[PDB]
Image (spheres, coloured by chain):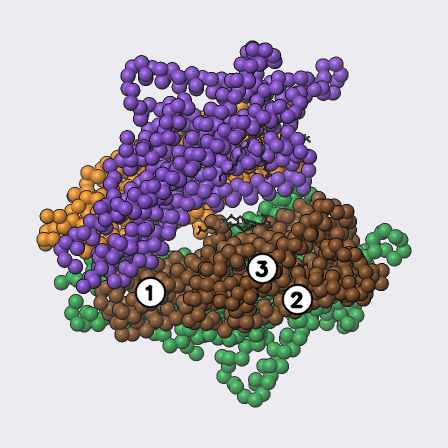
Chain colours: A brown, B purple, C orange, D green
Amino acid sequence: IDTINMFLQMTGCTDSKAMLYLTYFEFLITFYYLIATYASIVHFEQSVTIQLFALLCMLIECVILLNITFRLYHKNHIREMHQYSRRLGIPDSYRSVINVITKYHLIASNIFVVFPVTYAIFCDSVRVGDPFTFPFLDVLPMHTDNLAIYACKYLVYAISVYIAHVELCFINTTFIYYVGVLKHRLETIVQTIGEAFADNDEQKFKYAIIQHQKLLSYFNTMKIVFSKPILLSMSFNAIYFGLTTSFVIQAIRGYINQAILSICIASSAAAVINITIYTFYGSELMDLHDKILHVLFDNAFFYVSKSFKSSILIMMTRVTIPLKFTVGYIFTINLNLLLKILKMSYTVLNVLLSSET
Amino acid sequence: KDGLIKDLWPNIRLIQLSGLFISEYYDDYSGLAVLFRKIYSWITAIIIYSQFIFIVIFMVTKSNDSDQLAAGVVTTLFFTHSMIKFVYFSTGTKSFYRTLSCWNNTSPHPLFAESHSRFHAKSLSRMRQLLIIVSIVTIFTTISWTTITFFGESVWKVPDPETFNQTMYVPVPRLMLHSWYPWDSGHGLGYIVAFVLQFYWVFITLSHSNLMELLFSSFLVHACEQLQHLKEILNPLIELSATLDLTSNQEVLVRSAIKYWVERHKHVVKYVSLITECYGSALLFHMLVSTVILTILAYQATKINGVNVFAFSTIGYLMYSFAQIFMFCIHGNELIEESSSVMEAAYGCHWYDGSEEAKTFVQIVCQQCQKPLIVSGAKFFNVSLDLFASVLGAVVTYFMVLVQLK
Amino acid sequence: KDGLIKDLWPNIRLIQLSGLFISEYYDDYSGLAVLFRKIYSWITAIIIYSQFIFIVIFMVTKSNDSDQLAAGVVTTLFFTHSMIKFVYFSTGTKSFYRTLSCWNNTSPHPLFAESHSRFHAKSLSRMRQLLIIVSIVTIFTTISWTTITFFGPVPRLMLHSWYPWDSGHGLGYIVAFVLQFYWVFITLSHSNLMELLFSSFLVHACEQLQHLKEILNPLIELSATLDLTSNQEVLVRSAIKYWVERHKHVVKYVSLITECYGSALLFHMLVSTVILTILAYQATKINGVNVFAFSTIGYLMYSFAQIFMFCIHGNELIEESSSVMEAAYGCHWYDGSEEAKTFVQIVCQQCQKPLIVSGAKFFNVSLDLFASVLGAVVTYFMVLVQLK
Amino acid sequence: KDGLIKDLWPNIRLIQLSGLFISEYYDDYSGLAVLFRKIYSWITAIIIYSQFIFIVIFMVTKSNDSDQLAAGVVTTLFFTHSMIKFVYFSTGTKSFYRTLSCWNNTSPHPLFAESHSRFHAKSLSRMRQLLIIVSIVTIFTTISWTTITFFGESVWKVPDPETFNQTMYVPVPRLMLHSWYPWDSGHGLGYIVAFVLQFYWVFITLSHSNLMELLFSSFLVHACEQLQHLKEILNPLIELSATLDLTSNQEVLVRSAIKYWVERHKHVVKYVSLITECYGSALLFHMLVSTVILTILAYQATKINGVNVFAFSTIGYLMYSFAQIFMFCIHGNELIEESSSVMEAAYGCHWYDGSEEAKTFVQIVCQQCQKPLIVSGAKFFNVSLDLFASVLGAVVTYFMVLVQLK
Ligand SMILES: CCCCCCCCCCCCCCCCCC(=O)OC[C@H](COP(=O)([O-])OCC[N+](C)(C)C)OC(=O)CCCCCCCCCCCCCCCCC
Ligand SMILES: CCCCCCCCCCCCCCCCCC(=O)OC[C@H](COP(=O)([O-])OCC[N+](C)(C)C)OC(=O)CCCCCCCCCCCCCCCCC
Ligand SMILES: CCCCCCCCCCCCCCCCCC(=O)OC[C@H](COP(=O)([O-])OCC[N+](C)(C)C)OC(=O)CCCCCCCCCCCCCCCCC
Ligand SMILES: CCCCCCCCCCCCCCCCCC(=O)OC[C@H](COP(=O)([O-])OCC[N+](C)(C)C)OC(=O)CCCCCCCCCCCCCCCCC
Ligand SMILES: CCCCCCCCCCCCCCCCCC(=O)OC[C@H](COP(=O)([O-])OCC[N+](C)(C)C)OC(=O)CCCCCCCCCCCCCCCCC
Ligand SMILES: CCCCCCCCCCCCCCCCCC(=O)OC[C@H](COP(=O)([O-])OCC[N+](C)(C)C)OC(=O)CCCCCCCCCCCCCCCCC
Ligand SMILES: CCCCCCCCCCCCCCCCCC(=O)OC[C@H](COP(=O)([O-])OCC[N+](C)(C)C)OC(=O)CCCCCCCCCCCCCCCCC
Ligand SMILES: CC(=O)OC/C=C(\C)CCC=C(C)C
C-alpha cells in the first residue's frame, strides 16, 4: 500500500489532483529528454561510445513515456480495480514481495545516480564534465563549467533516473498487488463454497456464484488494464536483452568504452525483473481455478436438493478452464513465455554480434 | 434478394462485373444475356492466363543472373495467387452458393428482434468498411505499380556477345511487367497496347485475389456478429425463466426462446463448417505460394541498400504479401475468440435464480461452447493470428540468418 | 467369417499369402497344410533377411565415398521399414487378432439397422478403395524399379547386393535379378499391406462414428414429449443403451488400434526421420534430369506417401470424434425427457476429448505431424542450400 | 511403520545410510545417536563439497584450451546435480515428510478391500523394480568410471615453458577426476588417498542424485496405482447402484462406497499437489543444468573420431543425462495418462442401467476427472514425455547444425 497509494494518486484515480500534475510534469520531462536524445543522435556529431549510450537513453525514455501514457489512459479501469480491491487485502507473501521490490528500486536508483560521481573520483584519465560523468547523457544546452553548473546538471539528469525507477516500480508492484487481490478473493470464494457444503445452503452457494462472477469481471478488467504494459515489456525486453548483451560482450572485448556497463548492468537488471514478475504471477492465475474445481467435488454433492446439484455442475464446468492472462491475441503470460523470450533474445544477440564484428 | 445475399450484394456485383465464372444472382436469364456473359468471362480468362504465360516465358528465356531469376519468380508467384483463385472460384461456385444461402429463411424471435436488427446493422457496416478498404488498397497498388516503372532505368543484364564472361545492359521496354509478346512491344502501337494490357491485367488480377479474400472475411464477419447477437440475448432469455412473483404460458415462452437460441447457434456452427469446406483449400494454396514468396522476398530484402526502386519494390511486395495473410488471420482469430467467449457470457448471466430448463440450457451451452469454432485451411492449420505470428517469426528469423551467414 | 474379419477379408488373405506369419483365419487346419504354410513362411523370411544382410554387406565393404555411403544408407533404411514390420506383425499377432475380434458379435439396433447398413457398405468401399490405391502404387514401385536401372564395371542389378556367387555373367546374373525382383515386391507388399490394415481400421472407426452421429436425431424424436408412456420409456432406454454400447465399442476399438500399431508407427517415424534427413542432403545434389534426380524424387515421394497415408486418416479420426458433440447438439434435446437430457449431458462431457492415435505416447498421428515433418525437411534443405 | 513409509522403506533406509540430512523414521532417539548421525551427515557434506570445490579449482586454474575447458565444465555440471540435490533435500525435508505421510491413516473400503490389495502390492512390485535398476545403473556407472581411467594416456596439455606458441604434454596422476589437492596426489600415499576419496565421492554423489530421482518416481508410481485402483473399482460401484429387482441397506452401502471413491480421489489430487510442491524446483534446477550439459555435449560429440576414450566418455555422459531426464519424464507422462483416462472409465460402465444416483455420480466424476493431473517443475514446464522429446529434438538439431556448419 506504500507504492500502490502513490500509483493511485499519480494516476488520477483519487480525488487529489496534485499528484496528477506531478505525473504531467514527469511526462513533460520524459518527452523533453526523448527529443533531446533524438536530436543528439541525429543532429549532432558524436562517437560510437556516445551513439550507443544515446541509443540506450532514448530507448529507456521511450519506454518510460509509454508506460506513463499507458497508465494514464486506463484511469477509470484502474479506479474500478481499486474499488474492487478495497474490501479484502492481499496475501502476506505478495506484500513481502512488494516491499522487497520497492526497497530494491530505491537502492538501485540511488546507486545508479551516485555511481557517475565515483567514476569521476576514480580513473584519473577522466575528469568531471565529459561523456560518462553524468547519470544521463549530456544533452543540456549548457556547457561544462565550474562545480556548481556540474552539480545542477547532475541533479537535472538524476531526476530522469528517479522518474524511470518510479515508473518501473509502479508497473512492477501493481501487477503483484492486483493478482494478490484476485487470489485472496478466490480463496474467500472457496471458503464460502466449503461453508455451503455444510448446511445444504443453496442460498450461500448462490452467493458464492455471485462472488465468482464478480471475480471474473474483475479479472477481465485486470486484463484490460495490463494488456499494454505487458506487451511493451515483452517486446522491449527481448530486443533490449539482445542489444545490451551485445554491448556488454563488445565492451568486455574492449571495442567500446567499458563504463557503458554501468547502464547495461543496470538497465537490463530492471528489465529482467519486469518480465519475470509478469510471467511468474501470470502462471499463479492458472492454479486458482483448480481450488474451486477440487472444492466442488465433495460427498455433500450427493445429499443436496437436485437444483443445488445443477449449480454445482455449472460452476464445475466453468472452473475446468484455467484463468489465462492472454494479451495481444497470441501471448499467454506465464513462465513458458519467459522460456520462449530468451531464444529471440539470443537470435538478436547473435545478429548484432556478427554485424558488429 | 434477401438474407446474406442482400448484405453481400456489392461483393457479388463486383464479382459478376470482374469476369469470374458466376451464373446465379442475375435478373436477365435470357439466351442472349447468358451467351454475352459467358463470352465476356471466357475472354477475361483467356487474357488473364495468356498474360500469365507471357510473364512466365519472360522468366526462364531471358533470365541470366540469380537476382533476375529471383525477381521473376517473385512476380510470377505474386500473380499465381490470382491465377489459382480465378480457377478456384470459377469451378467451385457450388460451395460459395451453399455458404451464401445458409441464412436464407431465418427470422429473429420477436423477443430478440431489436438486438438482431442492431447486430445486423453492425455487420453490414463492418462489411462495407472492409469493401472500402479492399478497394482503396487495390487501387493504390495498381497506381503504385504504374508509378514505380517510371523511376528507374529500363535496362536488362544480358551476357556480352563479344567478350567471354562479361555482361552488358540492354535497353528494355518500360512496362509494368517483364513479359514476352508475339508482337514488338518496344515502341509505338505495340508499346501502347502492351502497356494498356498490362495495366488491365494487373488491376483485374488484384481484383480477383482481393474479392476472394474480402468474401471470406465478410463471411467471418457475419458469423462473428451472429455470435455476438447470441451472446447478448442470453440475459433476457434467462430473465424470462425467472420465477419472480412458472405458468404454462411462461414455460412455453421460455422453451421457444431456448429453441430459437439453439437453432441460431447450430446455424452459426454449420455456417462455419460451410466456410471451411468452401474456402479451406484456397487458404492452403495461398499459404503454399506465400511461403516461397516470403522466403525469396527475405532474400531480396537482404540485398537492399539505400533508397531506390529495388528497395521500394521489395518493401511493397513484402507488405502486400503480409497484409493478405493478416486479412484472413485477423478474422479467423476474431471468430475463434467470439466463439470461445460464449461460455463466459452464458456463465455471467443470472442463471442461478432461473428455472430448471434454463439451468439445463446453460449447462449444455457451457459444455459445447468450450471448444472454439475454428476455420481450418484444408485441415492443415487453423486460421488465426497464431498463424500470422508464426509466419512473421519464420520470415524474420530467415532474414536474420541470411544477413548473419552471408 | 463375420464382423471385421469378413469386411477386411482381402487384406487378411493377402497377408496370409504374402509370407507373414498368420495362424488364424484359415479353414484348412490339417497336419499338412499348417506344416507347409509354416515352411513357406520360414523360407520367405529367410529370403528377405538374407537379402537384407547382403545389402548391409555391400553397404560397408564396398562404400568408399560419402555419396555412395549416403545412397547405401538410404536404400538400407528404405527397406528397414519392411524389415521391422515383418517381425512386428509376425511376433505380435495377438494384438491384431484382438483388434479384428473387437467387432465380432456386435449387432445393430432394430430401429437403427438400415442406417448401420448405409455406413457399413460405404466403409467397405473405402476399405477397398485404399486397397486399390496401394495395389497400384506398390505395383508401380515394382515396375518403376525395373525402368530406372537400365537408364544409367558393375553388374546391372536393381539393388547393389553382395552375393556368394558371381552375379556378373551367366545364370548367376539372372538368378540375382529374379531374387531382387521378388524381394523388392515382397518387402513393398508387406510395408504397404501393414499401413493399409491400419488405415482400414481408421476408416471403419470413422464410419461407425458417423453412423452414431446420424442416429442421434431419430433417438431424440423418439424421446420427444410431442403430443411419456411405459413403452416410450422402454424404447428410449433401449436406444440410449444401443447408442452408448456402440460409442464405447468405438472407443475401445480405437484404443485397440492405438495399442496394436502404436510402437510400429514410432519405429517407422524413427527410421523415416533419418531417411528424410539423408534425402534432404542428397536433394542438394541435383544436376538436371538424370538417374540421381529421379531416384531422389522417387524416394521422397514414397517416404512421404507412407507417412501421409496414415496422417490424413488420423486427422480424419480426430475431427470425426470431435464432432459427435455438434451431433448431440443438433438433435432437439430441449423437447426430450429428463433421462434424455442427462444422456445428452454425459455424452457432451465425454465428447470433450477427440480420439487420437498416439505413437507410444510420444506424438499424435495427424496432419499436423505430417506438416511438421515436411517443414523440418524443407527447413533442413534450405539450411543445407544456404550453407553450401 | 505403516502407509507410504513402509512401502518406501528401503529407499528411506538408503537415504539415511547415504549421509543426507534426514532425522525422522528412526527408533533410537537418544542423546548420542542423534549426535552421531549429525556428525556423520556433516562430515559427508564437508567431504562432498570440498571435493566439488577441488574439481572447480582444477577446472579454472589448469584449463588452457577450449577443449579442456569443455571437458572440465561437463564434469562440474554433471556433479552440480548431486550438489544441488543434496543441499535441496537437506534443507527441504519438511515437504518430503509431508508427502510421505499423506497416506497415513487411509484404509480401503471393505467392498474394495480386494482390488486395492491387488494394486497396492503392484505398486510395490514397481517400486522395488525401480530400486533395483537404479541400484545397477549407479553401481555400473561407478565401475565404468573406475575402468575408463586406466584405458588412456593420463597427459595434460600445457603451454611449453621454453618456446612462445607451442604446447606440450605433461604426465598427470591417473585419477578418476581432474582435481586439485593440498597434498601431492602424484604417487604413494597421496595417490592412494586421492583415488579412494574420488571413488567414494563419485559413488556417493551419484547415489545422492539417484535416491532423489527414485523417490520422485516412486511417489508418481504410487499415485498412478491409486488412480488405476479408482478406475477399476468403478464397475462394481456402478453395479451397486443398479436398480435390478434401492433398499436401506443398499442405499447406505452405495453411499459409503461413493464416499470412499470421492475421498480417495481427493487424496490422490492432494498427493499429486504435494509431490509438485516437494519436488518441483528440483526438476527445474535439473533441467537448467542439463540444458547446459547437453549443449556442451552436443558440441563435444562433433569431435568424435573412431573409437577411443573420448568417444566412450561423451557417449556415457549423454546416455546418463538422457536417462536421468527420461526417468522422471516417463512417470510424469504415466500420471498424466492415468489421470486423464478416469473419465473414459467412468463413461464405460453401465450408468444408463443404474439409478439417478449412478448417473449423477458419473456426471460429477466425468466433470471432475477431465483435466489431467500434471506435475510441473515450478510451473516452468510440464513433466511428461513431451519434455523429453522436445529436449532430444533440440539436442539433435543442435548437433546437426554444428556438424553441417563446422
Ligand atoms: C517489436 C519491437 C518493439 C520495440 C519496442 C520499442 C517501443 C515500441 C512501441 C510499441 C511496442 C508495443 C506496444 C504495446 C502495444 C500497444 C498497442 C496495443 O495495445 O496493441 C496491442 C494489440 C492488441 O491489444 P489488446 O490485447 O489490448 O486487445 C485485444 C484484447 N481483446 C481481445 C479483449 C480486445 O496486440 C498487438 O498489437 C500485437 C502485439 C504486437 C506488439 C508486441 C510484439 C511482441 C512480440 C515481440 C517478440 C516476442 C517474443 C516472445 C514471443 C513468444 C510467443 C510467440
Ligand atoms: C512462411 C515463410 C517462412 C520463410 C522461411 C521458410 C523456409 C523455406 C520454406 C520454403 C522453401 C523455399 C523454396 C526455395 C525458394 C528459396 C530459394 C532461395 O531463396 O535461394 C536464393 C536464390 C538466389 O540466391 P543465391 O542462392 O544465388 O545466393 C548466392 C548469391 N550469389 C550467387 C551471388 C553468390 O533464389 C533464387 O534462386 C530464386 C528462387 C528459385 C526458384 C524457387 C522455386 C521454388 C519451388 C517451390 C516448389 C514447392 C515447394 C513447397 C514449399 C512449401 C512446403 C511446405
Ligand atoms: C485501416 C486499414 C488500412 C490500413 C492497413 C492496411 C494498409 C495496406 C497494407 C498493404 C498496402 C500495400 C500496397 C502497396 C504495395 C505494393 C505491392 C507491390 O507489389 O509492390 C511492387 C510493385 C512493383 O514491383 P516491381 O518493381 O517488381 O514491378 C515493376 C517492374 N519493373 C521493375 C520492370 C518496373 O509496386 C511497388 O513497388 C509500389 C511500392 C510502394 C510501397 C511504398 C509503401 C510506403 C513506404 C513503405 C512503408 C515503410 C515502413 C515499412 C518499412 C519496411 C518494414 C518491413
Ligand atoms: C487418390 C489418391 C492419389 C494419391 C495416392 C496415389 C499417388 C501416390 C503418390 C506417391 C507415389 C510414390 C511411388 C513413386 C515413387 C517410387 C518409389 C521409389 O522408391 O523410387 C525410387 C526408385 C529407384 O530408386 P533408386 O534409383 O535409388 O534404386 C535403384 C538403384 N540403382 C539405380 C543402382 C539400380 O524408382 C524411381 O526412381 C521412381 C522415380 C519416378 C518419379 C515419378 C514422379 C516424378 C515427378 C514427381 C513430381 C515432381 C515433384 C513435385 C513435388 C512432389 C509432388 C507434390
Ligand atoms: C536458438 C536457441 C538459442 C537458445 C539460447 C538460450 C539457450 C542457451 C543454452 C545453454 C547455453 C550454454 C552456453 C555454454 C555452451 C556454449 C556452446 C558451446 O559450444 O560451448 C563450447 C565451449 C568451447 O567450445 P567453442 O565454443 O569454443 O566452439 C567453437 C566452435 N563452434 C563455433 C563451431 C561452436 O565450451 C566452453 O566454453 C565451456 C562452457 C562455458 C560456459 C559455461 C556456463 C556455465 C558455467 C558453470 C560452471 C560450473 C558452475 C559451478 C562452478 C562455478 C565456478 C565459477
Ligand atoms: C549452468 C546452469 C547454472 C548453474 C546451476 C544453476 C542451478 C541453481 C543453482 C543454485 C542452486 C539452488 C538450490 C539450492 C537451494 C535449494 C533449497 C531450496 O529451498 O530452494 C528452493 C526454493 C524455492 O522455494 P519452494 O517453495 O519452491 O521450495 C520447494 C520445496 N522445498 C522447500 C522442499 C525445497 O528457493 C530457491 O528457488 C533457491 C534460491 C536460489 C535460486 C537459484 C539462484 C540462481 C538462479 C539460477 C541462475 C541461472 C539462471 C539462468 C537462467 C537462463 C539464463 C540465460
Ligand atoms: C528395463 C530397463 C533397462 C535399463 C534402461 C536404462 C538403461 C541405462 C541408461 C543409462 C546408461 C548409463 C550407463 C553408464 C554411462 C556412464 C556414465 C558416465 O558418466 O559416463 C562418463 C564416464 C567417464 O567420464 P570421464 O571420461 O569424464 O572420466 C574420466 C576422467 N579421465 C579422463 C581423467 C580419466 O564413464 C564412461 O565413459 C562409460 C562409458 C560407457 C561405458 C560402457 C562400458 C565400457 C566400460 C569400459 C570402457 C573401456 C573401453 C574404452 C576404451 C575402448 C578401447 C579403446
Ligand atoms: C525499462 C528499462 O529497462 O529501463 C530501466 C532503466 C534503468 C534501470 C536506469 C534508468 C536510467 C536512465 C533513464 C538513463
Q: Nearer the viewer, residue D347 or A303?
A: A303
Work out how far the residue at label 3 is from the one at label 2, CA to CA, in angstroms. Answer: 24 Å
Q: Quadrant of the N terminus of chain B?
A: top left
- Name the residue type under label 3: Tyr
Which tag, 3 or 2, sits closer to the chain's start? 3
Q: x%, y% of residue D310? A: 69, 53
Q: Are marks 1 and 3 in contact (CB under 8 Å)?
A: no
Q: Is residue C316 visible?
A: no
So how many labels did they put on this image? 3
User: Dot 2 corresponds to which residue?
Assistant: A108
Q: Is residue A223 left or right of residue A65?
A: left
The chain letter under disc 2 is A
* Residue at image coords 55%, 20%: B55
- Name the residue type under label 1: Ile
* Residue at image coords 43%, 47%: C364
Work out how far the residue at label 2 is from the one at label 1, CA to CA, in angstroms. Answer: 44 Å
Foreground: disc 1 or disc 3:
3
Q: Quadrant of the C terminus of chain B?
A: top right
User: Mark 1 and mark 3, same subunit?
Assistant: yes
* Label 3: which secondary element: helix
Q: Is mark 2 within 8 Å of ligand 8?
A: yes
Q: x%, y% of residue D159? A: 83, 56
Q: Is residue D390 left or right of residue B264?
A: right
User: Dot 1 corresponds to which residue?
Assistant: A210
Which tag, 2 or 1, sits closer to the chain's start? 2
The chain letter under disc 1 is A
The chain letter under disc 3 is A
* Label 1: which secondary element: helix
User: Dot 3 corresponds to which residue?
Assistant: A24
